[PDB]
Image (cartoon, rainbow, N blue to C red):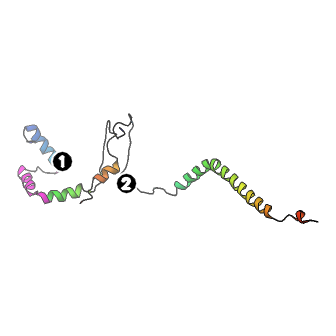
Amino acid sequence: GREFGHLTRMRHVITYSLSPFEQRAFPHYFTKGIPNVLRRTRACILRVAPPFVVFYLVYTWGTQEFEKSKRKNPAAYEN
Amino acid sequence: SHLDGTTPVCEDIGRSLLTYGRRIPLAEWESRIAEVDASVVREVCSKYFYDQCPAVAGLGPIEQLPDYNRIRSGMFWLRF
């Protein structure tokens, strides 16, 4: 059913590989990894962060508002 | 059997002179073969086969051809 041999039909695709004992496990890990991470972060920061920033603003206001509510009201004890 | 015929003998002579620098007589080949036993076969195969990175060439409907990591793992035995 789902086995290597009849999954799909592919033609004229040549793949070149290398032995894991002939290549480095961390090739250019920081020279190319760090720029790549920045690219990925930049592409997603404007789609992931903004919703969470709203939560932080709501969380701060709610915490402050709850504190203010418990605070003493001088006008209530006037007269 | 390969040395039956004038053309095979000439090819053997030329190739031997190009590669070995000399024509190896069949007597020397037989002596070298007779030197071979089970221990020699095991040792040489271990030297050249056991736990070695191979080169693979596939062509055609080779979707089932095992991944190179799997083939490399197949190039050694856990039991041994």
User: Which amino acid, mark 2?
Assistant: Pro
Question: Which image quarter is the C terminus of chain A in?
Answer: bottom right
Q: Which subunit holds the residue at mark 1? A: B
The answer to which image quadrant residue B46 occupies is: bottom left
Question: Which image quarter is the N terminus of chain A in?
Answer: top left
In terms of depth relative to the viewer, which is nearer, A79 or A35?
A: A79
Q: Position of residue B40 (x, y in %)?
A: 14, 59
Q: Residue at x 38, y 39 (%)?
A: A14
In terms of depth relative to the viewer, which is nearer, A36 or B4?
A: A36
Q: Which residue is mark 2?
A: A20
In the rendered image, residue B52 lying in the magenta stretch gets the answer no
Q: Which subunit holds the residue at mark 2? A: A
Q: Position of residue A33 (x, y in %)?
A: 52, 54
User: Which amino acid, mark 1?
Assistant: Leu
A32 with respect to B13 (left or right) = right
In the rendered image, residue B31 lying in the magenta stretch gets the answer yes
| Magenta-colored segment: predominant secondary structure | helix
Question: Which residue of the protein is positioned furthest toward the right in this rendering?
Answer: A79
Q: Which residue is mark 1?
A: B18
Magenta span of residues: B20-39
B65 with respect to B40 (left or right) = right
